[PDB]
Image: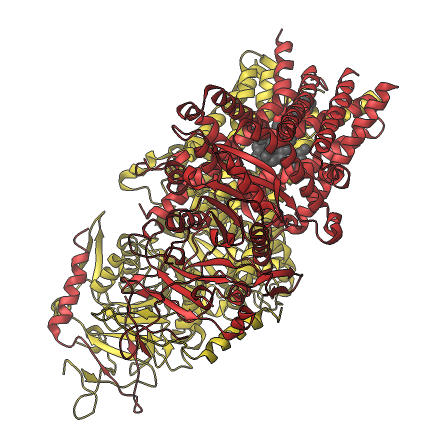
Chain colours: A yellow, B red
């Protein structure tokens, strides 16, 4: 219940502004267009079952930059009550072209969370009128790019009416359209086809704020509007970022907000879950079960270990929250503009930080000067999303993730000295330095997976062929050729073609790699059993058993073990495709490159018409002299220069990746003519396999087991601390 | 001297059309715009030192398709005299954006040739008024793409005046602008900066015909306008194709026309020469001397051998001539449209023949049904052109040549049975079949050069390292790694980047390959000298000496030997770059892929304005119901489909090329795990080098010597027949 404000509709005959409830002449309010329309009586019929905010919707045409809304004298309904309304929590939802099911899921999760907070009993912050402290800001990116089933859902809530959007106002290009309403209707069911909207006494009001950008700038500009724009006016305590389609759990927003009672917390995130469908029906898809296992282990092992140190690298799908005072200043300046100091040319970090979009913020929050903000991971809050079910869209999704992670980790390692310019105490500074070193160690390991997988596969298959001879010779040669053909084809198709065009090939390549992994598992088991009936296979069995047991125990400690059997084998079988198809495509597509009027003739009936023709000899001579003159007096734009720089930097990364991996391959296996060279050196005074292969094979597995052990200790510490 | 016709200027007061020499009201002549403007008196001053064609210039706006000009009632000045003028020779010049120096060179060569023909004494065809039998048709491609220094040269000749070009006439888009004049001024000198134009009693008139297309369609459309368009009206005996910048020799057009006195000749071409500059100054550039040698040998060996059989594959720069009756019908239909029979989908040959643009015509002229046309090569006629002097533009030029040659040869081999459906006698049919088989043999050899060069280099360097041990071990390993790095980088940069962006790398790669070739030459000489002080190096010395001697003798027989010393070493040194840089880039770039208004606000002084607003409750309810309705009722265009097909077919060619070359590499050198496989097979019961390397090394050189011998016999037969 309860609202009020003073509207700006239009002027009548007396000239004193009049309300509809109580060709026309208007008046710009302070120089910019603000209009107040009533809503249809169909909504009023539910609403009655009445103050000013429920019955009007306010359109504003924002013609300025995000960082100038207040100066230009633009406002929001929250500031214009008799007592200005103070917001505790601003929830940002970003759409690009998402359909109404995804947006419906996000809004329904938000509405359920707000209802939970409003029904809270013993709280100083939340209570019966807690909905007044929450603003839901839906920033859609382009009118041309929005779906009409989303604008139809937004309209059905009461927060959109067409007709009074304007392209320009006093020769000023309108940059954005803002629709403001407070709705009493809630979403109660979202089937595969329909969204159930209903309004009764049990519903809670939601202060929606629909922003519609005029043209599609990317997501960083949406965040620019959210943080530099409306957050400056509303002054929220916490700013929460959600994507359309990410449905928060029933208490996730409250449980994340509860994380900020520690005054040192500057940001927080929760768990992101794969949405397995109805009765886990989607778990039959190997691509979906693999992703389910990957998400569960990224949350259980990686996030807890990072949160112990104090710096988290929030996962792309999960919804995050930042304390607004934490990000004001340097972090937002780095996030939106980049390293401002820059000459006409291009620098590596400054021109490439857009690849690591949100992971910059986190870094700058932790290493902020004279401030001891920490990032913290909340396991009590979760959000479930749908994952790609087809190989091409899976590849296209992970292209962004892998490039962002690689660049963010390189940037954080290269600039770690900032940890010591911040305001943390000495112990936290040491912990953060150790964590950044460990994260770069992980990045370095992930950079050499191309060689690691091939070396493990080739050593294993050749060793079994050497030892037992039966049909493993032919199998070794055949699998070498299959690997080579698939890898060459993946390189060529990712450098030149698009994944949508060739889907059968990518599916076939994934199947080939799965069969390869099955063969490697068989070889390992066979060699181990024969040895039990040498030392290297003792090491392989002990190390792999240990790394499986640590995963299982960490899942049990986290109290979420069911993914360790329903989804493990699928992930194991698709791991070679993660190494060999996702990484190649991600590295081959780093930057997403993209390389007078004369007159008219209209004739009359007779075929006649009139013309302006050079008739005087003098003007013909003039034109002739002007062309006789041209025969006597005898880098392009910034966009293509930036495109050239991006292409150079994308192609220098692939070459270095391939060469540095083949260096290790050639050192271990003595490829590259090295075995020839040693042979001919001795002749101056080739073997099948050396002891370098044994040493490397052991080292790889020990690294895997060590990483599992470190992450197990991290997760154990996380759970123990949280439980105490 | 001597012209006349009836002009179409405009209507005066009496209404009977009036001439300027003897806002106005006009009249479409037969429904289309034809205007006749006078020329400036500056030209008249030279001209006097007078009939109708010299003093007027005729603009026509062509709004129809090339194949419809006569039906739509468009004409040319040649048909409209009292006695219609019959053309013997139509010279087509195509520009895209060439500057005035290139066009000036072409026009000056043409003018000098016409002057030679007009001064001819004992000829039935040519005489004092021979200029009346020649029409020079300059087809420029796009108004936006033409240079202004070219339109200033064309205007200075009298064949262009601006002002009366029209975009549309009676709602018909004007497709092309035709300017017609007969000029008495000639070009007498073209320095680096100025073009010397002069008019006196020694000058010869030229019937120019400047076509200016409205928008840039590519060159095949220009030929479509020339052949299906103006050639249908003029009815020439011979149609000659020239590019802007190609300067014909002083008698080249007459000597090519002389080839057509044999009634069986359907086409002909002459020699194309590299323009070495002033006093051969450009011969200092290695890239230019290499091209000079390449052109001289392509003319001496390839063209004569082809001309003996009866089918030539005219070189891209050379100017060619077709007997018009020969190309009418099937050849032009295949050249312009492709295989007309085609479903909605894409077929290989039909959708890729545009890559082999002019080489289609030649094929269809020889294999025309019931006709015994032959193609013949004329050594008495030549044209000199400028060649690229920088590596990126050289690469970009050869991209087109290599793809065209490869596709044309594949097409000619696959469809050779048509030779037997033509009208030739049995012996010529056998000769043509043999020639097509030989040409496909050459194509097949050129497809495996990637493996041939590497195998020769690796066998040679490893053999010298094995035999003498001193520092050839290190050199072998170092050169293997240099080759690998350069090849991988070339693949990655040609698949992903543009040659303009990375010029230093391409120059460095060419230098690296030149040093590699120097090392290989040294190794061959060293091994041969040591053997003389085994049998394989006897074969190498005999075979390479024989293939050099045959080249030298063929150059002497042709009476053009000077390129065998001034330009030979440069070509030898750049040959690895031809194999390894031009071919990779050509194959990696086969197809040149390229992947509501709202309202406005203007306010008065008071800030007030008027609007159309939905005021009635009924219309707001209507809009709400129309959005509540959308929530209840719950492949792209041809261009991108063709782009996807082109990408698929371009990337399937690279993969097959690489795999089929590596198959040969792995068979000969036992790479690919094959030596491992044989070793472990024997263990079930690796060497440095095998005898396969010896056999392959001999075979490659014998093939080279055999090709030299065949081409020597061909050139000898050509010269002997011509001399008899
Ligand atoms: C060094 C590489 C530098 C690394 C740079 C970049 C890393 C690239 C990794 C390639 C792995 C090569 C492994 C290797 O040792 O090469 C082997 C094969 O010799 C070759 O065929 C070399 C081909 C060059 C590959 C360049 C990649 C370009 C992709 C398109 C490729 C187009 C296909 C090119 C061929 C038509 C070496 O042969 P060998 O040792 O002399 O034979 C002795 C065998 N024996 C002892 C049993 C008798
Ligand atoms: C078969 C190929 C199928 C052809 C398909 C396509 C043709 C490609 C030509 C490559 C030439 C390979 C030559 C070869 O035999 O491979 C050798 C190296 O083993 C490898 O490293 C294989 C790497 C795959 C190359 C695929 C090209 C992709 C370019 C990007 C590449 C990314 C870099 C990938 C590595 C990080 C084989 O090793 P080996 O014989 O087991 O060692 C024994 C040596 N010994 C006897 C002296 C002890």
In the rendered structure, the answer to whether residue A242 lies left or right of residue B275 reads left
**Residue B670 vs residue A297: left or right?**
right
**Would you place residue A391 above or below residue A74 in this image?**
above
Relative depth, front residue between B454 and A169 = B454
- Give the quarter the ligand 2 occupies: top right
Q: Nearer the viewer, residue A351 or B218?
A: B218
In the rendered image, the residue lying farthest to the bottom is: A14
Q: Position of residue B133 (x, y in %)?
A: 47, 51
The quarter of the picture where the C terminus of chain B appears is top right
Residue A706 is situated, as x and y percent measured from the top left of the image, at 59, 38
Residue B162 position within the rendered picture, expressed as x and y whole percent measured from the top left: 44, 70
Is A614 placed left or right of B664 in the picture? Answer: left
Can residue A662 be seen here? Answer: no
Q: Is residue A347 above or below residue B673?
A: below
- Give the quadrant of residue B325: top left
Residue lying at the far front in this picture: please name it: B122
């Amino acid at each position: 219940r309860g609202d009020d404000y003073q509207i700006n509709s239009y002027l009548g005959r007396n000239g004193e502004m009049v309300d509809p409830y109580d060709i026309r002449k208007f008046k710009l309010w302070n120089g910019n267009f603000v209009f107040d329309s009533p809503i249809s009586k169909t909504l009023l019929d539910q609403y009655a079952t009445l103050p000013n905010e429920f019955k009007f919707m306010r359109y504003q045409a924002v013609t300025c930059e995000p960082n100038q809304l207040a100066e230009k004298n633009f406002t929001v309904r929250q500031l214009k009550y008799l007592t200005p309304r103070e917001t505790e929590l601003m929830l940002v939802v970003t759409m690009y072209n998402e359909d109404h099911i995804l947006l419906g899921r996000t809004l329904k999760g938000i509405m359920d969370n707000v209802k939970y907070m409003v029904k809270k009993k013993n709280s100083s912050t939340w209570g019966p009128d807690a909905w007044k402290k929450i603003v839901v800001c839906i920033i859609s990116d382009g009118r041309s790019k929005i779906n009409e089933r989303s604008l139809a859902l937004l309209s059905s809530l009461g927060c959109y009416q067409d007709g009074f959007a304007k392209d320009e106002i006093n020769e000023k290009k309108v940059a954005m359209h803002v629709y403001e309403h407070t709705t009493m209707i809630n979403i109660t069911n979202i089937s595969e086809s329909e969204v159930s909207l209903e309004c009764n006494q049990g519903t809670v009001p939601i202060q929606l704020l629909f922003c519609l950008k005029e043209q599609n700038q990317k997501k960083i500009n949406s965040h620019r509007w959210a943080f530099e724009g409306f957050a400056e006016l509303l002054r929220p305590n916490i700013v929460t970022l959600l994507d359309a389609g990410t449905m928060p759990g029933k208490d996730s927003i409250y449980q994340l907000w509860r994380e900020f009672r520690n005054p040192n917390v500057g940001g927080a995130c929760g768990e992101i879950r794969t949405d397995l469908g109805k009765r886990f029906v989607k778990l039959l898809n190997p691509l979906v079960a693999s992703q389910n296992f990957e998400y569960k282990m990224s949350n259980i092992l990686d996030k807890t270990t990072e949160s112990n140190f104090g710096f988290i690298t929030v996962l792309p799908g999960a919804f995050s929250a930042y304390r607004f005072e934490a990000v004001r200043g340097q972090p937002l300046q780095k996030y939106f503009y980049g390293e401002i100091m820059e000459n006409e040319g291009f620098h590596f970090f400054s021109s490439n930080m857009y690849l690591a979009e949100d992971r910059i913020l986190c870094f700058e929050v932790v290493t902020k000067k004279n401030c001891n903000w920490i990032l913290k991971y909340c396991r009590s809050s979760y959000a479930s999303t749908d994952v790609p079910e087809r190989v091409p869209e899976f590849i296209l999704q992970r292209r962004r993730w892998l490039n962002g992670s690689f660049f963010a980790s390189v940037y954080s390692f290269c600039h770690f000295y900032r940890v010591w310019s911040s305001g943390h105490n000495i112990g936290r500074k040491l912990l953060l330095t150790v964590e950044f070193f460990y994260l770069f160690f992980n990045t370095l390991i992930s950079w050499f997976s191309l060689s690691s997988f091939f070396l493990v596969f080739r050593i294993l298959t050749v060793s079994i062929a050497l030892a037992y001879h039966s049909a493993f010779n032919v199998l070794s040669v055949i699998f070498l050729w299959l690997y080579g053909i698939c890898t060459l084809s993946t390189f060529i198709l990712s450098l030149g073609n698009k994944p949508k065009s060739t889907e059968k090939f990518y599916v076939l390549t994934c199947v080939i790699f799965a069969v390869m992994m099955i063969y490697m598992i068989f070889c390992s088991i066979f060699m181990s059993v024969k040895s039990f009936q040498t030392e290297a296979f003792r090491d392989i069995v002990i190390s792999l058993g240990s790394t499986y047991c640590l995963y299982l125990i960490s899942s049990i400690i986290y109290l979420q073990p069911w993914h360790m059997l329903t989804s493990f084998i699928q992930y194991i079988l698709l791991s070679p495709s993660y190494i060999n198809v996702l990484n190649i495509y991600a590295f081959c597509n780093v930057h997403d490159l993209s390389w007078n009027p004369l007159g008219k003739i209209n004739t009359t009936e007779d075929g006649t018409f009139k013309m302006e023709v050079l008739v005087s000899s003098s003007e013909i001579q003039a034109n002739y002299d002007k062309y006789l003159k041209v025969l006597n007096d005898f880098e392009p734009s910034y966009d293509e220069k930036k495109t050239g720089y991006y292409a150079n930097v994308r192609s220098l990364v692939i070459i270095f990746w391939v060469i540095t991996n083949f260096i290790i391959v050639a050192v271990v296996l003595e490829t590259g003519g090295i075995a020839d060279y040693i042979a001919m050196k001795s002749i101056s005074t080739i073997p099948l396999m050396t002891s370098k292969a044994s040493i490397y094979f052991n080292v790889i597995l020990w690294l895997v087991a060590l990483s599992a052990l470190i992450r197990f200790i991290g997760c154990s510490i996380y759970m123990i601390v949280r439980f105490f």
